[PDB]
Length: 222
Image (spheres, helix red, strand yellow):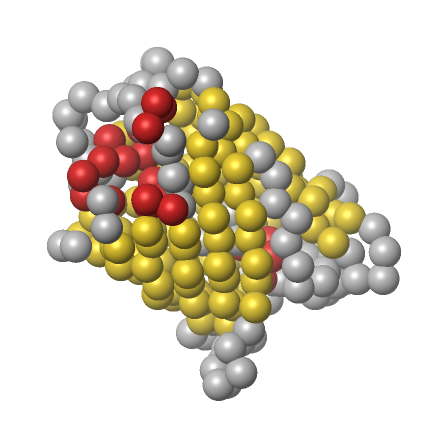
């Protein structure tokens, strides 16, 4: 099936066109993924200058096909089954007391690379609040994601809340809303409702002079 496209180490390209309050920017990302361990290792660069948001607010947007699916549930794996034709991923993210993101993304194979292309638009943000005022710590507090099949769209939806640590105290809520649909026409594994558990560690690279993000991530399903 598609599951076989991930048996070993795959390369990962992430491209991101964004516009937040008219602050326009871009992020490109390279890395690889090993679905057998749901291990992601990734570097992201603001190839346009300084990132007008804090890196953590883009972690979610910046590949759930790489999550390690234990043997007994390989049949619930929409993300690998949509491949290589891929899936669209649309999200809407509400930052409690600030604006929000609208993100479209195409997650397909291109040659041997898994490519996550993304458009991100944001409106209604306060220019001195925690997002545009760069007020969040460079840490990540993951949260599980409840995956639910959307039989009418032939794919899945999801709703989950990320907590962002606020410099000097507090947490910024980021209410997440997600649907995925398949791109190709093959059949797809519509899955039973389940969880995806993510641990995420953002580091820097001491030899990169651009505004950037090193990210190591693990995702496994249950």
